[PDB]
Image (cartoon, grey):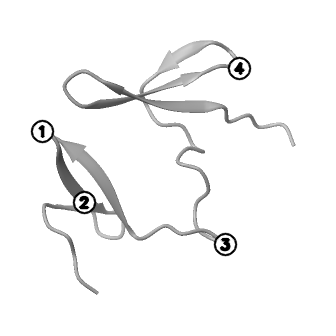
């Protein structure tokens, strides 16, 4: 099934996430439509996404409404 998706995640100075493609051989930054493994359906992925900011602070964001958070939500 032609599509391709050989992207690797790498850490950069300060605290950024860069991606690279071995197929074509080019360094990228913007996450394409098919990264972070699978996405729902027979998988384990919550609604909130874990992000890294500052020296090493964990921030969470919601795709439902679109609001960033700075605390671990309860359930």
Residue 2 location, quadrant: top right
Sequence-first tag of 1 and 3: 3
Q: Secondary structure at mark 2?
A: strand
Sequence-first tag of 3 and 4: 4
Sequence-first tag of 2 and 4: 4
Find disc 3 in the rendering and name its residue: 42
What's the CA distance linking mark 3 and mark 2?
Answer: 23 Å
Residue 71 location, quadrant: bottom left
What's the CA distance linking mark 3 and mark 4?
Answer: 28 Å
Q: Residues within 10 Å of mark 4 (few under 14, many from 20)?
A: few
Residues 33 and 70: in front is: 70
Sequence-first tag of 4 and 1: 4
Residue drawn at the location 60% of the way across and 45% of the way down? 34
Residue 68 as seen in the image, left or right of residue 23: left
| Residue 13 percent location from the top left of the image | 24, 21
User: Residue extending furthest top?
Assistant: 25
Q: Is residue 46 above or below residue 55?
A: below
Are the two marked residues, 3 and 2, in contact with CB atoms closer than 8 angstroms?
no
Q: Is residue 49 above or below residue 10?
A: below
Find disc 1 in the rendering and name its residue: 54
Position of the N terminus, as image quadrant, is: top right
| Residue 11 percent location from the top left of the image | 35, 28
Find disc 4 in the rendering and name its residue: 23
Q: Is residue 75 above or below residue 25?
A: below
Q: Which mark is residue 60?
A: 2
Sequence-first tag of 3 and 2: 3
Q: Secondary structure at mark 3?
A: loop
| Residue 35 percent location from the top left of the image | 55, 44
Q: Which mark is residue 5?
A: none
| Residue 63 percent location from the top left of the image | 36, 63
Q: Residues within 10 Å of mark 2 (few under 14, many from 20)?
A: some
Q: Is residue 25 above or below residue 4?
A: above
């Amino acid at each position: 099934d032609p599509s391709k998706g050989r992207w690797v995640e790498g850490i950069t100075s300060e605290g950024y996430h860069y991606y690279y493609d071995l197929i074509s051989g080019a360094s990228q930054w913007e996450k394409p439509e098919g990264f972070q493994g699978d996405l729902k359906k027979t998988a384990v992925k919550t609604v909130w996404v874990e992000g890294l900011s500052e020296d090493g602070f964990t921030y969470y964001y919601n795709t439902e409404t679109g609001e960033s958070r700075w605390e671990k939500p309860d359930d």
